[PDB]
Amino acid sequence: LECHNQQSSQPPTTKTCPGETNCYKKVWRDHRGTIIERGCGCPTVKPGIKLNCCTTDKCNN
């Protein structure tokens, strides 16, 4: 599938992963602030972190 992989404020870039069929989003908070990041695949979650996944393209625009 093909997905976008830019972080918080950088200009647009993308990558290709033929073998997987889904893309993912991750979000987390700490004492000083919070951050968000994008990727290929759909990994496990843990308490304190939040995660989400999609199957259509250009979902995590």
Image (cartoon, helix red, strand yellow):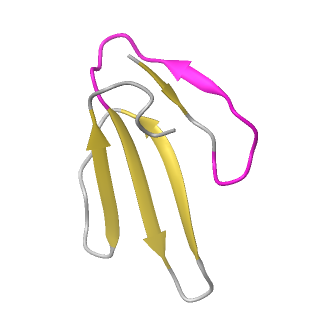
Which image quadrant is residue 45 in?
bottom left
Q: Does 1 sit above or below residue 40?
A: above
Which image quadrant is residue 34 in?
bottom right
Q: Does 21 sit above or below residue 36?
A: above
Residue 33: horizontal and vertical position, in percent?
60, 81
Q: Is residue 21 magenta?
A: yes
Kindly identify the residue that appears in the image at 25 percent across and 66 percent down: 46
**As rendered, which of 22 and 45 lies closer to the eye?**
22
Residue 8: horizontal and vertical position, in percent?
65, 54
Q: Does 35 sit above or below residue 30?
A: above
Which span is picked out in magenta? 7-22
Residue lying furthest right: 11
Residue 36: horizontal and vertical position, in percent?
53, 59
In the displayed structure, does residue 10 sit left or right of residue 46? right
The rendered magenta stretch, by its main secondary structure, is classed as: loop
Residue lying furthest bottom: 31
Kindly identify the residue that appears in the image at 49 percent across and 44 percent down: 38
Kindly identify the residue that appears in the image at 44 percent across and 63 percent down: 27
Residue 57: horizontal and vertical position, in percent?
38, 24
* Image quadrant in which the N terminus is located: top left
Q: Is residue 13 magenta?
A: yes
Kindly identify the residue that appears in the image at 46 percent across and 38 percent down: 39
Q: Count the labels in the image.
A: 0
